Length: 102
Image (tube, rainbow, N blue to C red):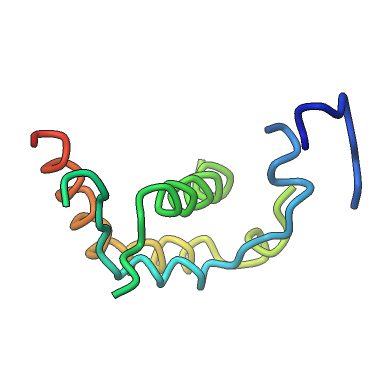
């Protein structure tokens, strides 16, 4: 329904401005490992994981190197909390590495 309308502004350039902000706490769901379909719990899939990584990347490139809730937090706090999520992230990286080498 977006494509047919030329423009519409109800309260990819408007992806983050129009949508409601997401807090840092949501990324805790990353602890569940991904399950791919073709190669073969609720099994967090590829596309939602891409969505999470997209939002986290758009947070980081704004903070470290619009947003309201993210910018009223300490930079040291943000770095520490991102570090906190390092160990369930490298497992995803290793798993997709094995996906591609497969």
